[PDB]
Amino acid sequence: PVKNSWPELVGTNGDIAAGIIQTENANVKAIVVKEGLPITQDLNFNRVRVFVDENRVVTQVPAIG
Image (cartoon, rainbow, N blue to C red):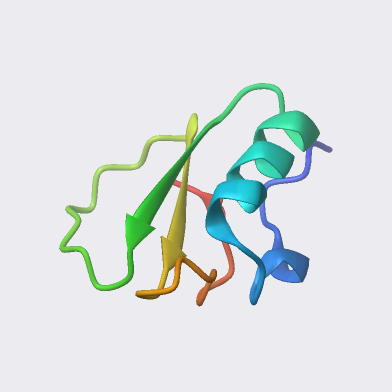
């Protein structure tokens, strides 16, 4: 089963986390986004949103969707 969530990257730099994610799961694009960005309920299994704070630290567990 391919890895689809990265709890161990919470608290890390989001741009570094995006690189790791795209290496561990070859079928996803990782996107660093500011936490709280309004998103619709569109499920994109090839996307991992990496939610970060004002210092670009990951604040939520990244997962596909």
